[PDB]
Image 1 (cartoon, one colour):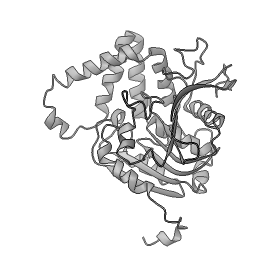
Image 2 (cartoon, rainbow, N blue to C red; image 1 turned 45 degrees about the vertical axis):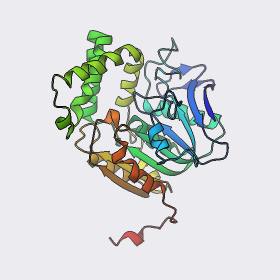
Image 3 (spheres, rainbow, N blue to C red; image 1 turned 135 degrees about the vertical axis):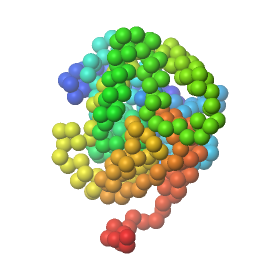
Length: 327
């Protein structure tokens, strides 16, 4: 079954003390009543349409069709974050949408949306990289018992690199409106090393021309106010803020965590995503040796999905860890 609809969940108060009278969460559900739940947390530029249609396939469709997380064994739920322009409460929908939205807000709304629909356990929690940020917060609130977690291209807090990125983008938008959106979009190419893409796409002038083309599309289809909102969301990410016990919590969580980090990435360095994994009781890391950009980690699934599948297929009872002093 395939369902796309909108919850109405009443009053929501952000961290900043601002109010939405009727919190709306657009979502996509897919699968059968009783199956293991997988919750996907989408990334800044994505949305709830995880599986999508046959004619309009979804962000994750290829990964699901390829059988890495197969439809036949799983049930899928995904919310469009608040502030996104694709159906949930946002500046595009709500003329009194809060000025200061944080990531912790986005999460706390989605957990209420997960509970609105009667779920209790989450077998697989998955996201990168804003998705991964959602994921880690969610694990901290501990409103759910969650068996398996995959966190891709995200860390414990927004870096100075990312604030610089986000500020540079913010400025361009002030100066140029829609035109600033192109730059913001183009800006992403500067955050990572492209490998034999340099080979295949010779074509400078033709990369630049492609950049321009992607930027121009983006500036016509993604609402501007919402984008600025989501830039604050990123700037607000830090699991440790106002908190003392984050690691402690994570160290007594039974959840099996996989962290994935990508090669030569300045926005989300492998170094630091691995170190976030290692904060948990049960943790593991995969280093993925190709990178078409944080924004397109779905596009290069060939290089990482099989390790996901490997991870998903633990069905060895948890070992209590002093057995690992070896080494």
